[PDB]
Amino acid sequence: EYVSVKYKSVYAIEDSWVRDGDYANTNYGTANTLVVKKDGDGYNREAYIKFDLQNIDITKYQNIFLALYVANSNTSIHDTQWNIGYVADNTWSEKSITWNNRPVTTNTIATVSTVPAGSNVMVDISQAVFNEIKNNSKTLTLHISSTTRGADGKTDAQFYSKEGSDPLKAPQLMLQEK
């Protein structure tokens, strides 16, 4: 059939990315995109995103999604995938996180195929977030990283950040109402 599904958006309260190499001490907490790319030393980009889980009544919802909006993507973005990792450590801050102080990723919650600039990814992380809410976790950190460098290396992409123009394209959990 045709179906109309209703979602509540929960926007990230912090987000940044980190780069290794000479940039391993650089902060990007105000950057209006989150760069993600796997590659050799000095050219890795990984993203961190924080959400407030307080004031969420999980009895209203059947699924929970992470939505990232792709601002720009390189030529062969199809050659890699994106790992969505769970980060237990919520003590980092977007205005001080760097590659050298980034928190540890606990485990991979999902691996999704990429989409080009102007498209949107919607990653089902229902059990991940339901578990954190049931466990009285007040705050959720997701780590975004790329699985593959790729044959030609043109596999970097950038998501809209909370500091991007359109607040509707900022990182967000989507709460699917029952």
Image: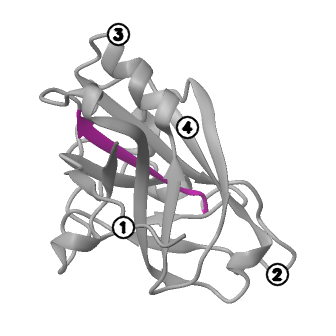
Asked if residue 136 shows in the view, the reply is yes
Disc 1 marks a residue whose amino acid type is: Ser
Please say if the residues under marks 1 and 3 sit with CB atoms less than 8 Å apart. Answer: no
Q: Label 2 vs label 3: CA separation?
A: 43 Å
Disc 3 marks a residue whose amino acid type is: Asn
Of marks 1 and 4, which one's residue comes earlier in the chain? Answer: 1
Indicate whether 175 appears above or below 42. Answer: above
Q: Nearer the viewer, mark 1 or mark 3?
A: 1
**24 to the left or right of 6:** right
Indicate whether 151 appears above or below 140. Answer: below
Q: Which residue is mark 1?
A: 4
Q: Residue furthest left?
A: 55
Disc 4 marks a residue whose amino acid type is: Gly
Q: Nearer the viewer, mark 1 or mark 2?
A: 1
Q: Residue furthest right?
A: 151
Asked if residue 88 shows in the view, the reply is no
Of marks 3 and 4, which one's residue comes earlier in the chain? Answer: 4
Q: Nearer the viewer, mark 2 or mark 4?
A: 4
Q: Label 3 vs label 4: CA separation?
A: 18 Å
**Which circle marks residue 76 in the picture?**
none
State which region is magenta.
Answer: 43-52
Location of residue 160 (image quadrant): bottom left
**Which circle marks residue 152 in the picture?**
2
Q: Identify which residue is drawn at 46% across, 66% down.
A: 35
Residue 147 locus on image (x, y percent): 73, 54
Location of residue 53 (image quadrant): top left
